[PDB]
Amino acid sequence: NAMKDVVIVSAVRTPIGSFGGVFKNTSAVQLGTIAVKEAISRVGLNLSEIDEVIIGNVLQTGLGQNVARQIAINAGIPNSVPSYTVNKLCGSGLKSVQLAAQSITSGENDVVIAGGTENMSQAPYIVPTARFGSKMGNILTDGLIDAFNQYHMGITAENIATKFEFTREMQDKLALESQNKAENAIKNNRFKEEIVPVDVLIRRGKIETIDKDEYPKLGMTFEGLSKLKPAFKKDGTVTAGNASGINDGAAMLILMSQQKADELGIRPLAKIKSYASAGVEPEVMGTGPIPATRKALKKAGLSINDIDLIEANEAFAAQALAVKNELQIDSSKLNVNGGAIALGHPIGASGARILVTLIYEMQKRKVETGLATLCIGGGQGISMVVSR
Amino acid sequence: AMKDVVIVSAVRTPIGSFGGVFKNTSAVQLGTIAVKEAISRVGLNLSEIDEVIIGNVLQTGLGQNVARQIAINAGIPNSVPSYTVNKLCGSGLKSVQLAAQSITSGENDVVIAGGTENMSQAPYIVPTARFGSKMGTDGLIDAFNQYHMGITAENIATKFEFTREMQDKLALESQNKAENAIKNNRFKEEIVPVDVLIRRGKIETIDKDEYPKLGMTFEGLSKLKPAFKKDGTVTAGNASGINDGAAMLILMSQQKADELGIRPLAKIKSYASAGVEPEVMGTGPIPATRKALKKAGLSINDIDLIEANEAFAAQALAVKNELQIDSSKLNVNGGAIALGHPIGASGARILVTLIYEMQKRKVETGLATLCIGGGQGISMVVSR
Amino acid sequence: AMKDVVIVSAVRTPIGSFGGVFKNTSAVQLGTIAVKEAISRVGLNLSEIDEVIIGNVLQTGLGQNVARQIAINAGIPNSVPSYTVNKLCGSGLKSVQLAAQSITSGENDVVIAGGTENMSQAPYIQYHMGITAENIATKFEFTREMQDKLALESQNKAENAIKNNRFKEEIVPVDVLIRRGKIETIDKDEYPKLGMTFEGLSKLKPAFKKDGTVTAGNASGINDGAAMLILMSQQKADELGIRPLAKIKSYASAGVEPEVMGTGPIPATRKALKKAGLSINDIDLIEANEAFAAQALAVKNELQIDSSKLNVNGGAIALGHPIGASGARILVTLIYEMQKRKVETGLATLCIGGGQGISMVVSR
Amino acid sequence: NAMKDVVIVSAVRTPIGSFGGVFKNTSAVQLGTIAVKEAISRVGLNLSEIDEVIIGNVLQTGLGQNVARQIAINAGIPNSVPSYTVNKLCGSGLKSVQLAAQSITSGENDVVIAGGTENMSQAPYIVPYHMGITAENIATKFEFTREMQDKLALESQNKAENAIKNNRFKEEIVPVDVLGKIETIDKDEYPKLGMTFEGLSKLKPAFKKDGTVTAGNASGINDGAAMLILMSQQKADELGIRPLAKIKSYASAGVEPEVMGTGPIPATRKALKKAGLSINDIDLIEANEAFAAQALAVKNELQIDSSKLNVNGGAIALGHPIGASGARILVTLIYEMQKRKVETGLATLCIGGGQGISMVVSR
């Protein structure tokens, strides 16, 4: 029995909203439903062809909630189809894609919808504290709740900065360039193809169509970033300016076996070449994408020079610098349309979001090979190589 | 204001530790147990009940009426209105006050009042916006607002020059008082034992308060580190805890009690509330008590027993000293430092404890007082 | 002896629509404006205020007290106790009830009560209530057409009232900042839809159920606004030389059976009338809050209310429903209209949770 | 390319402890670690051969918690090895094995540790249950009386008692040491000996007034772990390790809203279809018994022979540590297939109220 090739035939993302911003009233289920219906519609896919739905989401109102199933139902997918919600923190959205591909290669499914969604704006009001944050004193601080685990992650980033010797200036420079790259991409409408617009109510009797990312900060300067106060550690280097934000958004892809796509007459946007995940030593927590990527590259028989475009999620500039330096990624190939520092980081979605952004840019540049990588827990990373 | 209001029944569950004996017994269950026992003890007909007013702070959301859930669970008719009071620390005593004024108004003849809280379960079912407050150390959530109140306590300690040693001495007295009370089964009359159930199968029976630290010595407190300020004076040993429990009282007009052949445990003589200046946050019980005493036509020397809730030794010292309360009249069976502080229940709990002790001692007058928010206090005078 | 309770001052801000005129005017600011104006209208000295009780639903902070912040902002001494009432839709009327209770008990002589809400500024914001309405519609057999025509009539009355500046006496204007250095005064409600028609209502899609009858057109919206009243004992009002606007005759609250959820105003009103020794026919004007036409039909029909006596200047379906404030808002509206019509007896009633209702009878 | 066959070469479980019972002080991590070390030790597996660890758990899945990874670290597995905690409610433990199998078939991994662990004693039980009502609705919908449910529960107890009397679980259990005296726990705690139909009929309904579901015809709240080691057939041959069983097929499926809780029915039909088998070809079935009402529906609709079903007792008797049960029933199936020397087995349970998962294995 032969192993199947998995292709991506459709891929879309909502704009990314700021915390308490445009999507404050548009739930994670709504955002996911919009992206799923659009993914399906763009390729005219019959709902009866969908075998499974696997969707990343981190912040749920309790045990027993299946956000993926709610979305699939809202999208009109038959109740007989199984849906699974993936909570793997930072990497949920890319892990969902990986799980979908495995299920195709195993012969279990021919057509799988995969992605991620998150609404972090709504979480403080509907998510129980035990699922919304972690306790401090995990190191006074103890007895305090760390919203979204942001403080624990920032300390991890500070520790990376210390061990790898990344200064405040170096981190701010990367952050500035992320913003520069997003601003130029948005000026050139680079995201037009991948974005599904989202309608919101801004006032009674008035609907606005949101088709632009909210989080990028226009006209940022190095001087401005230099003025910001440390966010997590006194005399630290990590600030709100060189870290990503708290954000809302969704991203969805449709996967098929090459054979199924052919049968349906649907042309692939990309092919999945390899993927891998890996753990790290506790001395370098947060550096997961490095061994994962080396492992995925080795599986594909490729080196980093063979990769035309890289998307490495930018939760923190400190961590982004480590990934870039240890993998020897050329500045010109990395997060070319901006990274999460500019674009935002809706946690359950980002892994899928960066894959969407990657595929559309590979297509625009007519390049052959790309890579998406990010954390999947503080101690682990996941990486996926795709080809056109 | 012609109707005289009496308390005819008063009961409380044991108070459980955080994640302790009641981690599987919700605020609704605890409150239902207390309500059913309070009714049962005086043989009250369920049709006599006109209203239910119950304190509770930590809720899964808006639109939740914990009081009504308890009333329904207790078999009280659906036509009876029920209200949940969320006024923080003071909710259980404010509920009694509201019940009393609804009787004096002529609106009601019989009202069930009290409070219930399960803080152990709260992290798992209460959204973060309702579970805690933001710090500023910013973007960090202060669970149960304990850090904010701890800092308020430190500021009182600074303002009034209450040393670490003075706070620990009060805390020690509280612990030792609770221990001796428990050794003498002092709370037996007021406690309703709680059967822990899983799918209506009994796993255990709780009839003793879990939180007191038996055999406490002064050195046991002096060895602890500050909890809120580096080089501060407030510790986990001289502040109360996070706790689970319920307490319920039944109020009636005197005429109604007489008609029903039910002897009062106590009469409510006065109550009052008051705000404080921002420089002395957390000191609410002081002006509230002075106000309530003036309404009763009494002075502090006319009061035989006082229950002033002990959230922080620092704050308790201020209340004791500013009101000039004889230490031997204050929290005589132990205070919240030893017994625990289930926030929605405590105001009603201390009133229950006060009433039974007045009766055992056969004295005439008592008062109960505590905060109703950082900026406010509430106080109630009762007589036997 | 029991104190008789009077209302000596009553004011409401305009009602703003969602994301409308008051999007940058918080529940506290709206509340403070209404409170300051209620005080100045009768020239009341700040030292006479004994307590402040204010309804509010959406400021759910642990340890947050909007009523006290409002009191502080209005220059009321910090020694005065203030309480925020969260009782959902009944909050603003419950506040007045608690105020009255504390005066009759002898605790207080002068109490400020009301409600305030800014639903625009809610970080996260009707589903279950909507289903409850859909269930009432089923049980009492109220059709889409029946609900839409009630909505239409509510709009008509509001249009008529506003055309005749009916709300001029009761409204306190609110200054808002449009840009740096430039403020604009809002003195008119924003939510009424002018010229809405039957055919326009009939085309709307059901809001909750797939084949349901409740829509955005026959239910209220979400809104921003505040309303404040000053209550005194009659004796106190005399000593200060302030004439009552109204006298509180009775009030009551009641629960309902699970089958009839959302019908709380019905037994609550019957109870209050019974305490007043009155019948529905003795009441000249009735304000029953209109969150849903389906439930408004139930209240109207079961209480056998003459439609010419009910919500005569429009109900919430037309005027808006700032939840923590509505209970107080309708009482304010009821009082001023009683004065204009020179009638003697009025009644306000609304839900206080899905399972309960509250009702109050006033006289002039 | 070529698709690899997945075999199970090691399989173990802890005893299942009662709520507040023997494992009151033994965490999901501790139970899980014990099960992993023993599974590894039993086949003399070099730690450097392990490619991935996938472990079910429900109650310890808070932000930034990774129970599987802590377990791997405690078991001495290199830190470079990725570990994943699966939270899929009741199906977590079987879903983990399924995910392990797919990662081997994909060529991603050669050796994967999979299973589940749960300590429900150390978690809060909050009621002021959703499963219990689903069960009542199944009872109503399918017309299962109180008496029918209790009859099933009693048979489950009787089968468990028979198996324990014959030391049936001896091969599959790893003993757990608990506390200054140290007692080795080597027997399941939860079965109720001397169980009678009458004693069952005396219990009160647990979820609904005049309900049929009780604490006696529903499974308990329990503590335990179960772990398995999966390899490609090629990798097993290379290491010289003989398989206990081979994974033939698996599948999952959603249900219609009217029949919530019946997931195992369409999931099993789907898995049998993929295997090229009918129910009558299956020699032994383990279908998890969360509620008698639900087990009755599964058994009837799939037309399962009672003499082949949960032959050593089901969860009503043995206990239901939720994140572990999916793995636990597979371990129990595999050992009993080997004792009876039969060829084909099926394990199935819910994975959410709306879904089920099933796996067919052969010997």
Image (spheres, coloured by chain):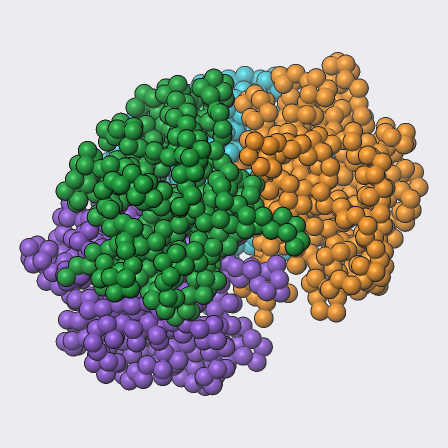
Chain colours: A orange, B purple, C green, D cyan
Residue found 8% across the figure and 54% down from its top: B260
The answer to which image quadrant residue B272 occupies is: bottom left
Q: Is residue C15 left or right of residue D239?
A: left
Residue B249 x, y percent position in the rendering: 23, 59
Q: How many marks?
A: 0
Residue found 39% across the figure and 70% down from its top: C79
> In this rendering, does residue A204 appear at all?
yes
Q: Is residue A292 left or right of residue D326?
A: right
Residue C359 x, y percent position in the rendering: 27, 43
The answer to which image quadrant residue B276 occupies is: bottom left
Q: Is residue A235 left or right of residue C235?
A: right
Residue D61 x, y percent position in the rendering: 57, 48
> In this rendering, does residue B84 appear at all?
no
Residue found 56% across the figure and 41% down from its top: C20
Q: Quadrant of the N terminus of chain B?
A: bottom left
The answer to which image quadrant residue C90 occupies is: top left
Q: Is residue A138 left or right of residue C312?
A: right
Taking A137 as reference, is A286 above or below it? above
Taking A177 as reference, is A73 above or below it? above
Residue situated furthest right in the rendering: A305
Residue found 65% across the figure and 25% down from its top: A37
Camera-nearest residue between D175 and A87? A87
Residue A25 x, y percent position in the rendering: 57, 39
Q: Quadrant of the C terminus of chain B?
A: bottom left
Taking D147 as reference, is A231 above or below it? below
Camera-nearest residue between C130 and D31? C130
